[PDB]
Amino acid sequence: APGETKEDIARKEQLKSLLPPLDNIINLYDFEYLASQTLTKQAWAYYSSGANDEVTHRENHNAYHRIFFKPKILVDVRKVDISTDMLGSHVDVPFYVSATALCKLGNPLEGEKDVARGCGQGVTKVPQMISTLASCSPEEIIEAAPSDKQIQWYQLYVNSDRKITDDLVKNVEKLGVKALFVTVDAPSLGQREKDMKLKFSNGASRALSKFIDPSLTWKDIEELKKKTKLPIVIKGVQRTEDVIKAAEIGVSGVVLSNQGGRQLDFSRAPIEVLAETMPILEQRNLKDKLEVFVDGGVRRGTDVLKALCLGAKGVGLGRPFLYANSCYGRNGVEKAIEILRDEIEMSMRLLGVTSIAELKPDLLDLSTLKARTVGVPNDVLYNEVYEGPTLTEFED
Amino acid sequence: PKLDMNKQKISPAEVAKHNKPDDCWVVINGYVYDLTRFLPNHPGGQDVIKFNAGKDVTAIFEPLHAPNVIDKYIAPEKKLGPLQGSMPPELVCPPYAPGETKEDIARKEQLKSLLPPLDNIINLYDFEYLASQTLTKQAWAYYSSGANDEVTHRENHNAYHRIFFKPKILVDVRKVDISTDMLGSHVDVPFYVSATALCKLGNPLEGEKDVARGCGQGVTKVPQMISTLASCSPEEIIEAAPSDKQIQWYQLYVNSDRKITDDLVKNVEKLGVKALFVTVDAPSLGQREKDMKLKFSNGASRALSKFIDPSLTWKDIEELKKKTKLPIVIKGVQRTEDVIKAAEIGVSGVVLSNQGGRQLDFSRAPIEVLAETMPILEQRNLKDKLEVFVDGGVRRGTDVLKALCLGAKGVGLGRPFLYANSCYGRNGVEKAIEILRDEIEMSMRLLGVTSIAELKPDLLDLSTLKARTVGVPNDVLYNEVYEGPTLTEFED
Ligand code: HEM
Ligand SMILES: Cc1cc2nc3c(=O)[nH]c(=O)nc-3n(C[C@H](O)[C@H](O)[C@H](O)COP(=O)(O)O)c2cc1C
Ligand SMILES: Cc1cc2nc3c(=O)[nH]c(=O)nc-3n(C[C@H](O)[C@H](O)[C@H](O)COP(=O)(O)O)c2cc1C
């Protein structure tokens, strides 16, 4: 606690349903606000933070905005269809809760259970990665799913102990789960400063966690494809050339990620990555060779749509659901599933197409995609004195 | 210093009569000195000694200059003779508090070990924030400011942000190696301490010495380039320095009295510093507004000083080269052609620097330069003729990294070690070091590489290097009118 000024009772009156009626809620940002000051300093830090200066973090969201829509007109759109298949499941929606370690932190009672409950409770059901570090037992989780259609997914951090892993691997292949997400981006953890900052007060490879095997490789991989039947997605790719390495070692999926930028500041945003990639995957003919996935930044229908439009087999969010959960639990979480589904939906029509398959790039103004500028330090001295036009008054 | 002479005598209200900065005598410690000559030529504005002339002064001189100061820069016969008795009070100078207010107590008692534990600091920025609350309205002023509209200084840093990474994945990075080597010696870390002047302002007490300490003492250890305008002597800073395998570099401002210089050099070469970095981007003293803005709440070329000689020229560097065994580095190059010229005279390296924005506002980011330049160095088959350095504005290891992949042999920080030393002294400095090295190692890891030679342009997303932008000066009236959307509530 101990940033926990008995103010846990500012927090308390807030949680203490100060929260609005879970349907006054309007977008994913709404969750996130309520989250930011009801959760614990400690939880909120863990969750919110990002690598160092938190550019890549923020950059991932913004890069969506170099991208604008060319939409399509007088296209009959009474009915739109928004579903698609991932790793040959077929899939309500085309986005996916994703793997968000320690939810017991903002959901003490329920944890990532409240998540699955969430992705299955509702007319809509969506996938789920299960962090290799949940607050819960894979079993404890994998069991609170209602619909037996709800799909489910293992993200896994290899180990040091090629044993413990070779165990969980099949331990989980035992319990159901339709694939493997190996999270390569995370040999060390990143220096998530908002965390450290209260984990006290309020040659140092102390920040390589040894759950993660900092020594992972393409062998260790081309291995594990053999030690299993499940498919494999390499979560955390960060360039073109690595992508091709999955393509060649012929694995299955990829996520273009950087862990919500919690990893390395000045990593690019995945949407940039996607965008340069996909088209190369035309000219090699590894075109269908590989499902590609994208994450982080994602807060709107539009975001998602854009991703798709660009190539994504499927798009992932963490935080949003992560807040969702921690304060309406599984209900919160499914409203989320609800929310984001509608944005996908209305936009789809205003966009002029009816199947996710119909989502091709030509629907995108992609001409500014690389306008990723840094302006010059505006002029302190002159702005300070300058003074602007003013609006007419009102009387007396 | 001292002198004594033997002979002369003198007086507690008749040398009170030279105050006219035309005719200038003063009394320092025991002794009396004719100024009139050196006046216009004295590093920190000339000015401050018009405004104090015909006094004692020790208040003012003592705690902020180098020792052997007199007995280096003045002739044996300005060294006039003893004061007999003293002088009366105003007519012996209280030092030296431009803008200070019995508030060096909001200050004092903030320093009031009120300052966090050194293990609390997490980046370079916090030193600077601390520093900024504790240092002296001038110590802050001076350390912190840059020329003019302060634009090259922010740009030096911001420029790093138009570079992004392309990291390598699945690479065994259990062990990584940030050491590298520089200019002949081999080094622990790929970056150094640039020279800063007067640290005794922020560390009134050991100044440049605690820096030498902070980079010698720990297990990771680092190159200190020493300023020709240190608060301490070099002798001091060099027999200050705790470690043997520690390494120290001299920065030269060449005097107009090319002798004084030639002695500086031979002497430093004897305490075996290891390189000389001749700083060339200060023929005039650039103009540091916030620092001026002090005096005034209390020429045309009052910015020259026979001290920093403003007429040094490649012939001069080429003639330096023959009087010395130390490798020469030219500090403050700002574009590709003067880099090649250095190459063509075969000096042994250059620093791309613009002194951290203090000199010429609208100098470039030395990052951007280095980018444009290095490849050029290739196409002239003049690749490794030349070690390239780079400074200004570097605040996180990713920065350092970005420069290394770019070709830099090495990178310098200035203020952060200053602010660090200032608040915290030698552990301050080391602590910084440590902070930085960790960042580097850690990101060097995330990037998918294990040693410094594997940093390379193939790791960088350069595609928006050049995107320095200026946005159209935009829309007070509309912005004023637009109400943006809004997040939901909680319920009273
Ligand atoms: C007599 C031989 C002297 C020598 C060799 C000398 C040398 C120096 C040097 C290297 C500096 C650092 C300034 C910078 O940032 O550019 C300095 C600054 C300073 N000097 Fe001296 N100085 C001398 C005499 C004096 C005298 C007579 C005074 C009378 C007060 C004086 C007062 C100061 C002060 C107050 C500063 C710091 C102010 C600032 O630049 O913000 N010095 N001097
Ligand atoms: C609080 C938190 C915990 C995370 N834990 C994991 C994890 O255990 N394993 C994993 O592969 N990704 C982890 N991630 C990364 C995500 O799966 C995902 O890449 C990310 O959140 C995408 O960005 P976004 O949150 O803004 O939507 C986590 C992210 C957050 C915010
Ligand atoms: C307070 C101060 C004093 C300086 N004095 C000198 C000096 O005497 N000689 C020199 O060559 N450079 C001097 N410099 C410039 C640097 O050595 C260096 O180029 C600069 O500090 C690099 O930028 P940074 O402070 O953003 O890291 C000084 C810089 C500062 C900030």
Image (cartoon, coloured by chain):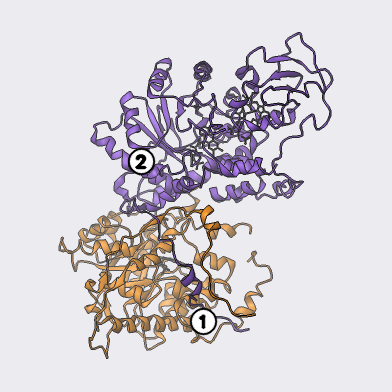
Chain colours: A orange, B purple
Q: Residues within 10 Å of mark 2 (few under 14, many from 20)?
A: many
Q: Which image quadrant: the C terminus of chain B?
A: bottom right
- In which chain is the residue bearing label 2? B
* Percent position of residue A57, x then y: 43, 62
Q: Outermost residue toward the front?
A: A396
Image height of B424 relative to B301, above or below: below
Q: Looking at numbered disc 1 in the image, what kind of residue is underneath it? A: Tyr
Q: Looking at numbered disc 2 in the image, what kind of residue is underneath it? A: Leu
Q: Nearer the viewer, residue B463 or B31?
A: B31
> What residue is rendered at 73% in x and 50% in y?
B106
Question: On residue A328, which mark appears?
Answer: 1
Q: Nearer the viewer, residue A185 or A130?
A: A185
Question: On residue B371, which mark appears?
Answer: none
* Percent position of residue A370, x then y: 31, 60
Horizontal side of B221 relative to B458 (left or right) equals right
Name the secondary structure under disc 2.
helix
- In which chain is the residue bearing label 1? A
Name the secondary structure under disc 1.
helix
The residue tagged 2 is B370
* Percent position of residue A5, x then y: 68, 67
Horizontal side of B400 relative to B218 (left or right) equals left
